[PDB]
Amino acid sequence: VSLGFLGAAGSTMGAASMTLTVQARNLLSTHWGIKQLQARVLAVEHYLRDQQLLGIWGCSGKLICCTNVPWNSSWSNRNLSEIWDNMTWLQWDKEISNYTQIIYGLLEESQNQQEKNEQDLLALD
Amino acid sequence: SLGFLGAAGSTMGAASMTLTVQARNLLSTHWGIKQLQARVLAVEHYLRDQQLLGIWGCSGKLICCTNVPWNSSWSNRNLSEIWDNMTWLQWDKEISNYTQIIYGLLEESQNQQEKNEQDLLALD
Amino acid sequence: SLGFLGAAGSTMGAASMTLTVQARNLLSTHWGIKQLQARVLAVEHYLRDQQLLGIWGCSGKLICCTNVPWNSSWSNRNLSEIWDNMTWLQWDKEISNYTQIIYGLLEESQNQQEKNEQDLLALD
Amino acid sequence: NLWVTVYYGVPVWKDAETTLFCASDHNVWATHACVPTDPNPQEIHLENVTEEFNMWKNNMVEQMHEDIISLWDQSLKPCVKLTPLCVTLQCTNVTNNITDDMRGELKNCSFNMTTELRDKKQKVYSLFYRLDVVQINKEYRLINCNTSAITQACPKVSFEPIPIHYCAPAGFAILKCKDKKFNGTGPCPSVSTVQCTHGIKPVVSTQLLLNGSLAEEEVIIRSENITNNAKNILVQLNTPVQINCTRPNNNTVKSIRIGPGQAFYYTGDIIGDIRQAHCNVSKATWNETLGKVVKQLRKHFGNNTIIRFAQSSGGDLEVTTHSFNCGGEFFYCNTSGLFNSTWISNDSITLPCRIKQIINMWQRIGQAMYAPPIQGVIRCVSNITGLILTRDGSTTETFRPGGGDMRDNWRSELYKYKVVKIEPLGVAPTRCKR
Amino acid sequence: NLWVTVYYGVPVWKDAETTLFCASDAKHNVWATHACVPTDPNPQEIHLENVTEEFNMWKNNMVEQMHEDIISLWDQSLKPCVKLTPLCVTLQCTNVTNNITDDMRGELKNCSFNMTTELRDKKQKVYSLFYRLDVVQINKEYRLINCNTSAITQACPKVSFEPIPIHYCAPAGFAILKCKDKKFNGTGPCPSVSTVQCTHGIKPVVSTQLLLNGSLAEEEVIIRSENITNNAKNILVQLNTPVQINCTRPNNNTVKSIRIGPGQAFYYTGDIIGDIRQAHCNVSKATWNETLGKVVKQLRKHFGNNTIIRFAQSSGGDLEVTTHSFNCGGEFFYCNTSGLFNSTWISNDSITLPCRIKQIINMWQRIGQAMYAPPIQGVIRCVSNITGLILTRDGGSTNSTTETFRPGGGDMRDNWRSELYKYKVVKIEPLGVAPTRCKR
Amino acid sequence: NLWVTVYYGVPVWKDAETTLFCASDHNVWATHACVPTDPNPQEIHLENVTEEFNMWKNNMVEQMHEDIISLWDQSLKPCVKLTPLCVTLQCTNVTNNITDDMRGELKNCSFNMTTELRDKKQKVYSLFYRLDVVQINKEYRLINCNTSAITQACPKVSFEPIPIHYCAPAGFAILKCKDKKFNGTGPCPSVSTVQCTHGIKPVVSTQLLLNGSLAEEEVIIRSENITNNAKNILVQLNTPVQINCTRPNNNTVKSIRIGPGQAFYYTGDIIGDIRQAHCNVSKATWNETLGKVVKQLRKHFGNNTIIRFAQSSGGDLEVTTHSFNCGGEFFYCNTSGLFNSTWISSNDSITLPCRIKQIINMWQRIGQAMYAPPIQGVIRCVSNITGLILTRDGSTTETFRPGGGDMRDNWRSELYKYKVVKIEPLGVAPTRCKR
Ligand SMILES: *[C@@H]1O[C@H](CO)[C@@H](O[C@@H]2O[C@H](CO)[C@@H](O[C@@H]3O[C@H](CO[C@H]4O[C@H](CO)[C@@H](O)[C@H](O)[C@@H]4O)[C@@H](O)[C@H](O[C@H]4O[C@H](CO)[C@@H](O)[C@H](O)[C@@H]4O)[C@@H]3O)[C@H](O)[C@H]2NC(C)=O)[C@H](O)[C@H]1NC(C)=O
Ligand SMILES: *[C@@H]1O[C@H](CO)[C@@H](O[C@@H]2O[C@H](CO)[C@@H](O[C@@H]3O[C@H](CO[C@H]4O[C@H](CO)[C@@H](O)[C@H](O)[C@@H]4O)[C@@H](O)[C@H](O[C@H]4O[C@H](CO)[C@@H](O)[C@H](O)[C@@H]4O)[C@@H]3O)[C@H](O)[C@H]2NC(C)=O)[C@H](O)[C@H]1NC(C)=O
Ligand SMILES: *[C@@H]1O[C@H](CO)[C@@H](O[C@@H]2O[C@H](CO)[C@@H](O)[C@H](O)[C@H]2NC(C)=O)[C@H](O)[C@H]1NC(C)=O
Ligand SMILES: *[C@@H]1O[C@H](CO)[C@@H](O[C@@H]2O[C@H](CO)[C@@H](O)[C@H](O)[C@H]2NC(C)=O)[C@H](O)[C@H]1NC(C)=O
Ligand SMILES: *[C@@H]1O[C@H](CO)[C@@H](O[C@@H]2O[C@H](CO)[C@@H](O)[C@H](O)[C@H]2NC(C)=O)[C@H](O)[C@H]1NC(C)=O
Ligand SMILES: *[C@@H]1O[C@H](CO)[C@@H](O[C@@H]2O[C@H](CO)[C@@H](O)[C@H](O)[C@H]2NC(C)=O)[C@H](O)[C@H]1NC(C)=O
Ligand SMILES: *[C@@H]1O[C@H](CO)[C@@H](O[C@@H]2O[C@H](CO)[C@@H](O)[C@H](O)[C@H]2NC(C)=O)[C@H](O)[C@H]1NC(C)=O
Ligand SMILES: *[C@@H]1O[C@H](CO)[C@@H](O)[C@H](O)[C@H]1NC(C)=O
Ligand SMILES: *[C@@H]1O[C@H](CO)[C@@H](O)[C@H](O)[C@H]1NC(C)=O
Ligand SMILES: *[C@@H]1O[C@H](CO)[C@@H](O)[C@H](O)[C@H]1NC(C)=O
Ligand SMILES: *[C@@H]1O[C@H](CO)[C@@H](O)[C@H](O)[C@H]1NC(C)=O
Ligand SMILES: *[C@@H]1O[C@H](CO)[C@@H](O)[C@H](O)[C@H]1NC(C)=O
Ligand SMILES: *[C@@H]1O[C@H](CO)[C@@H](O)[C@H](O)[C@H]1NC(C)=O
Ligand SMILES: *[C@@H]1O[C@H](CO)[C@@H](O)[C@H](O)[C@H]1NC(C)=O
């Protein structure tokens, strides 16, 4: 059966991939309503920032999105099976937290170039 | 055309030709609070529907074709009755009890498809 | 390597390479109301534009070619004049009156395409 | 065989409760706080749609009620508080020119009022109506002294109703019933969609409904349950009855300072003779109108029954008389000149009216308002567009004026509107597969 | 040679500070719960296997948020109540001597004063009783104690001060991590955790010295502190069994009221039927002695096996701080706890704690927002459970080998820390990357 | 043969009116309701663009005006009300050690005021300036007791004009004109984009502008319409004029409890001689400064036109004198000594006498008033005059007089170079590309 929201936390990275949906569908879900209003607004802003970034990278509607940027051993040098079968996502995030911005920048560059190349091919036939 | 909800009550098959009309109109001291509450409400509803469509594998589409088979127990009517005689209002009532079943199946189908895509890309 | 509006004044062609920079900078004691209003508006404007790209079938893209032909009555300038000489501010002024027309055509084209996709998939 | 297809932008809806906002075109109604509407708002007829309405469960009424009360209080928040006025008053009768109907109705009172300097007091003389004072044990006090705070309404802010348009938020729509001769409690075969309602004037009255919409063809009689003696009956007329109201006295208004930045207004004197306020209703118009009501009312009570009208039962003037705001002044008119019959050439009915300066609007305790007097002579003309009747419970039924629950006035203008939520995402089978 | 893969819906989080909202659980109560959002009675709790989370109850901002919300709810309740400014007059007072017993001597006074009526030009003579604690002699001339600080607002007679559980719920995008370890001492990693959306209805109980009506430890007394060897820090002790305490104000109070302006009713004690006796609380001796023995054993684990432990009284600097303050029946009690903390531990029969009653209350350590507590008609009896203790350590650098503990208390955030100790708020960070063998 | 292509993120903007929020970085302006900005804000120069600015048609001005008034009221809202001071005052002159220049002006008043208990009254002696007190028919009242209630400013809150930065909401940007010698009404060839403005000090003054931005090269003379005698002329200087303002009298401040939770502050007495408040400027600097103004002013009026300065016309003290805050005290200085000369083709000074007033009706509102507590001891402040507000008299030898009039023009000066625009990321253009 389902483990619930964050139920997979602590499970291995390759196991937790089966719970991406449950953790995605749970996003966006006298007087003194101002606190409630401020909370509702913030939840929306965070949601949209993640969606905007995925859109920039070309990952419009997918929970799993592959990108043409190669992985650098300088960011993390581990076996493919260590990463997916032994480590969890909390650990992984700590191991590569110092490369977050460079990876994101590279992803944006790749998609931008790809859009230009697609436009040129459409023009040529 | 007829304008917003102008097709309500018309045959389902005809009504479906003008989905853009509704798609455009959606998201179109304390008094200020009442307006803020209203604006937030419109946004939240809009986003929840888009979130859900994304989960099912469609984004930016008014007509989302998927791979979940239709169960004769949800409705045993034929296509000519559904599309030529029934309206959308009648239909929604007719299958109201199966909404969550269908939604659950749609999420599962996309989950499997994404995994399959990842494997094929890695495979070749 | 220019900044947020640093591309302004460059030719239309040159500026096409900075779209990421402009796009990523969108959305980023009773003066709490003024803050909420600012927050909310940034979101509403953002969503209206995304909604429109969605309707036109350009969701998720900074550059989207479509199937609406260009009418010389909107502009009869040379392709090189438009791209290698004029800037985007100038272009926007030159075709300001045709904006609504073009947007309507874009929505109609996409709606027709979606219907056609549905029929083709059903046919196999 | 068949597969699920998902459609977005599907033209369907569900009953819903959401918050509506104000729209419109220096007033008690806070118009400046409303957004302007478009000229000629778009109305869409829904062909082949039958909806179901129930006006008695309509929550638009509740919002109108709450918003109006809030605006009322907001208007008074920044105005002068007449707490220094709750003092022993020394009063005698005004006897200069009496019609013998006004005998004992108007009093001449004297009191010791505070002023600009904390060290000084004033001898102030003013006129009050009997209904605003009580005896203490010639020693009188104002009626609000043992129950409420008293706030003077701001002298420059008008009470005249301004049409207010209620608008649904995006994602919602307002359906309206155009079906003629529709009572509001069942299926409606003729429906259209709007984003904003017509402007509704927030007219406040207690027995007759003034300045509302009129029935399109015939008098319409509606209630939650016609056989229930505990319910009010709302009657919509298809013709207006014109009523001419006046307070025919030339009032000289005086003003004093009761502290820094404060001002208190009172009637200094009356020029000419002193006579009673009253309203005129033509006899012919009234008798035809009432006859139409009886005919339609028999539809529910029998083809051979007897219908009697009578004046209302006792209670506070708020419910026993017909009250209204005429040019800023507050009238309490006795309707017994009307509703006195049994059914089986410029003549008119004069309804005597009383005036009050201190009121407690919206059936509340603790919030009193002082309506400042108005300089000069007041006259206004209004349209009676409906009635609030109750019935008792043989061969004869008796109907009486009733009312006081303000939501029932609102229910009239809002009887044809419903708020629904748009539910654009739906599913249906077809032959398509990815 | 692997390409970067983007995943959304990843089960990770980071510590964060956000805004929380209340859930009432479905007429008048001081906590204004009608402003809260009703929740399901049985929120689902998700157990996290193989997850260890670092906790620190002393740096938990949820505590600060309750403190602020509680203060604000309190003020919203008083904002619309009777102003009572006109009561700050010179009073003519004598002692109530007619039927009191020895202990109650000189603790209750009979005052007369000239107060206003509805009409601005009229006055009335009013007689009322006041407790000694609220009346201060000037220069038979007295004034109320609040006159030289601020105006006093009368609490509304219809609004209850009884606590209603307030569950705190995280906003969308956030989650609350709950520590379940038995014997969790407030800090460090917690190997058994779970996720909830709302906390378990913490009650806004207000007290000093002793903690009332809280949760219990599952098996042993738990000692929690920021730094146990730092004598400047407080020690919070959670009990594994309740101690029943029965408090009363055994006098038949006849309540009277007058109008002091339009509306503006003022409430006061008119008189007392029968003889006068002091307020008090009953704690069983056997229960209390067992409870301390459990506490002493746990303290020795930190201060040394064969270390001598002595319990003593607090300093006399502040009436609220040095006594056990609570609001039984709507009255405010100030009980002397010395009978509970007078013992040296070296390895039907009950304790009676005398209590005083005060009506002018100045709480939350603020200055100038005094409240007048209306008297309560009849006789008051409350039964409460002691579910924890506050202690401070007082000693020097000398290795005397004996440690002394005193009740301490007085900082309201400690009551909140005691119950919120197991919760942490984190932000969900669903977006992230990892390498694999997939390329577009 | 071209197709419509849609682009998003296009660097296009349109003029717009939106709501800005404050950032900045106790005191009235020192409040914790703004969101502190970066120590390193960025600015992006826009090459090959020109944009039109119009400082007159600019709603940033209106927002500062509204925000400042609102903040002002929030500060005073929770402070002690002084209604009890409207009792009748018994007053005589303070002539103890009075210079002739101050004869009269300062009065010794006494009155019956309430105390902590409702039952008791107390007698108080206090000193007042003539400008705050009017005659009843030896009996006087405070000037505001017939028109408005008065609130005491909180003694713990200083009127310090702490710089406040304004920031655009996301989706908007602020364009800034970097073109030197820009008048503020036409095209600006050198423009840059910022997210936030420089911090602006919300300085209150009536004739001369104090502690604002200084012009880079030449005196800049600007107005909505030079030809219109109904418009003000704003003059921005290249060098500051140093002005030294003082209140030489040593005031001793006393306070009284007037009710529970309330205390009133007042001047008890003066230690030492009673002398007139005053401001000094260097005579040489002032003569140079006007010469620079005249030289540029002639560009609009002719080289055959005489420019003659004159003192302003009468009216309420606020607009006939130069008013400012100075240590928290409110000064009203006579500038007639600065605008006496007619201009036709060292170690000396100009002394401006000043008056002090404690009852303030700021922003020209009626119904509100503030009581300024006196400040203990001798007060001095030194400030930089960076500009002037002048008006035309309205067929030879034009006359200019001081006037500030509407305070909106104070804000205009700092904001003359900023414009708010909305970013519009979508657009289309033809290209040879089909799906
Ligand atoms: C049902 O609906 C009817 C309308 O169909 C309402 O009747 C209107 O009621 C309003 C409010 O009382 C009337 O407005 C007033 O009209 C006066 C007319 O004066 C004229 O003549 C004088 C010269 O003697 C001229 O100076 C003046 O300009 C006019 O040409 C005005 O004098 C009144 O002004 C006073 O009040 C305003 C308040 O904003 C102040 O600003 C003014 O300074 C002044 O003190 C006022 O404008 C309106 O005329 C009536 N219409 C008709 C056709 O009669 C009914 O009241 C409504 N029924 C109910 C119960 O609400
Ligand atoms: C144009 O710009 C100039 C330059 O900024 C402004 O001039 C300043 O004006 C302010 C306000 O009048 C002056 O600030 C005050 O200075 C007093 C003296 O400080 C000296 O002595 C203390 C001794 O402890 C030293 O710490 C300090 O560094 C100085 O050497 C202070 O006593 C004042 O304090 C006030 O607040 C405290 C709060 O705790 C109270 O206890 C005090 O009693 C008092 O109320 C205050 O700090 C500042 O010194 C001036 N600068 C200069 C260089 O002279 C102009 O005012 C401005 N013009 C306009 C129109 O805005
Ligand atoms: C917590 O860790 C344990 C291992 O210590 C996990 O148990 C293993 O799960 C895999 C996958 O189902 C099995 O093949 C192994 O045989 C299990 N090992 C043991 C010793 O039982 C457990 O699944 C983890 N929990 C979560 C939520 O991931
Ligand atoms: C208003 O019209 C409705 C619709 O015809 C009437 O509703 C019917 O009332 C009877 C009782 O008298 C019920 O038995 C029917 O089932 C109701 N029908 C429907 C469709 O709801 C209603 O009585 C009319 N009311 C008035 C005052 O005229
Ligand atoms: C209402 O009707 C009455 C009729 O009773 C009118 O009263 C007459 O008014 C005229 C002047 O308008 C007088 O000359 C007559 O003497 C009045 N008759 C009586 C019986 O006194 C009254 O004017 C009408 N009022 C309005 C404005 O409707
Ligand atoms: C009112 O009570 C006070 C105590 O609060 C009485 O004062 C005390 O009187 C006893 C003698 O009976 C002395 O031993 C104490 O030292 C006094 N206490 C103080 C603080 O001085 C007072 O006498 C009582 N008044 C009346 C009229 O009975
Ligand atoms: C509460 O439990 C924590 C966790 O075991 C204790 O923290 C340890 O304290 C020792 C002594 O200072 C250090 O050497 C360890 O490194 C600490 N561990 C961690 C995870 O921080 C803490 O001292 C206990 N406190 C009390 C009052 O019992
Ligand atoms: C996996 O990593 C370990 C070290 O942690 C290494 O010894 C082993 O050889 C690696 N195996 C693979 C997959 O090459
Ligand atoms: C209503 O029904 C008729 C058939 O009776 C049909 O011709 C008409 O098009 C329908 N209206 C709509 C809007 O579909
Ligand atoms: C401005 O024009 C020059 C022309 O030589 C060009 O080199 C420069 O790149 C242009 N600036 C921008 C931002 O395009
Ligand atoms: C009430 O006022 C009178 C005034 O003569 C005074 O004598 C009396 O003592 C006052 N009474 C009280 C109880 O304060
Ligand atoms: C007036 O000044 C003299 C010094 O010339 C001083 O001794 C005296 O005390 C002062 N008197 C007053 C009333 O200020
Ligand atoms: C106060 O000074 C004025 C100056 O004009 C003078 O007329 C007045 O008589 C003086 N009053 C006293 C009491 O000296
Ligand atoms: C205070 O009140 C008394 C009342 O007898 C009066 O004589 C005196 O003049 C007043 N004092 C002042 C300063 O107004």
Image (cartoon, coloured by chain):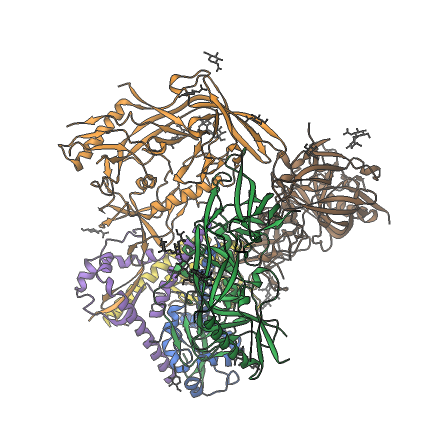
Chain colours: A yellow, B blue, C purple, D green, E brown, F orange
- State left or right for residue E407 relative to residue E364: right
- State left or right for residue E309 relative to residue A14: right
Image quadrant holding the C terminus of chain E, namely bottom left
Q: Identify which residue, D249 or D232, lies in the foreground.
A: D249
- Ligand 3's quadrant: bottom right
Q: Is residue E70 visible?
A: yes
- State left or right for residue D327 relative to residue E189: left
Q: Residue at x 16, y 27 (%)?
A: F344
Q: Quadrant of residue E128?
A: top right
Residue E429, horizontal then vertical, whole percent: 49, 58
Compared with residue E124, is residue A67 higher up or lower down, i.e. above or below? below
Q: Quadrant of residue A6?
A: bottom right
Numbered marks: total: 0
Residue most toward the left? F304
Q: Identify which residue, D63 or D183, lies in the foreground.
A: D183
Residue E164, horizontal then vertical, whole percent: 66, 55
Residue D354, horizontal then vertical, whole percent: 53, 57
- State left or right for residue E306 relative to residue B121: right
Q: Quadrant of residue A4?
A: bottom right
Image quadrant holding the N terminus of chain E, namely bottom left
Q: Residue at x 29, y 65 (%)?
A: F6
Residue most toward the right? E348
Residue D234, horizontal then vertical, whole percent: 52, 71
Q: Is residue C124 visible?
A: no
